[PDB]
Image 1: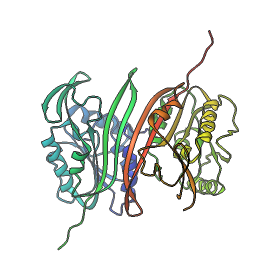
Image 2: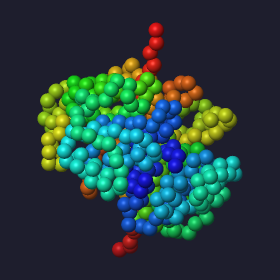
Image 3: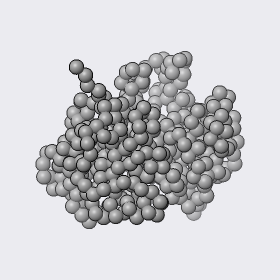
Length: 207
Length: 206
């Protein structure tokens, strides 16, 4: 493509989607920013759709689009209420996104992902875990939910245990689950991050 | 463009792209049907690879000619790199090192460090004690096992404390402890890896 996206797990997801027998249609729930990962899907022949709630992030993704001569098909919207029909998407991901919401909203959004996914369709979703350095920091607003100042702005972070995250996929076939603890030097200093990533397939139902 | 199997190497590539050093990369253990040197070649790098297996070398050369590039992979032993001191900006050994006894691991890592330029980056990963296969098969050394990945093959496993000691004289930019559960042969399996990206210090003498 030219540039490498920031979240390398989405290259694993792209490889799974390429291997799936379903046709190449993908939705990014939370798609904006200056390096939108839908780029690697468009570059690999996908029909893409994106949803983004932030005006600024949507503007950044559009600038990137123009600069690179892409149409990514990102629209303003709320991932808790997807404007797509039931069983319309082969593949859906919400990566680095879902945990910016309260747990009731996380459930709404995941339910929407499940709804729009075709039978046999793949979802990729990741979560902050209780192994993250910022678990229990900032202002507690709910169980496993904190309002934190990050880069000058208030952000909600929700955190899960692995037992808790598994419950979101108990009705799906988990193909890939990775629990990770990352220690990386960000802006001069070491930070510890905790994520669990899932790639799961929607069951087909009969009789 | 087939996507490579090891997504962490896309992260490594981005680190290498951000470095000020020129774009030369060595893959220690480079063969197979989907050589990750492909992503570096595609991004403008001068590439070098070392591969011990004739079969693995053949698979990578067929891939290369099928995809219309030259990866510059040659037969060799990663414990004895045919390159000069401080010749390479970037070096990786990914999915490779832990197929050896720990004495051999040390030799290979020492070689990576040797050929790496000051300021250069290394990416290396390891099997950890969280892997399901830790303590299975025939124990031949502390954290060394003869297992059946097939036929009798060597796997070495590390604790994180143990893995850290390999980079104690380097600047670790990125360290990721991973526990992966996925499907193999119709069953859920659990794998444990730790991945490092580290930078070589410039050294001076007072």
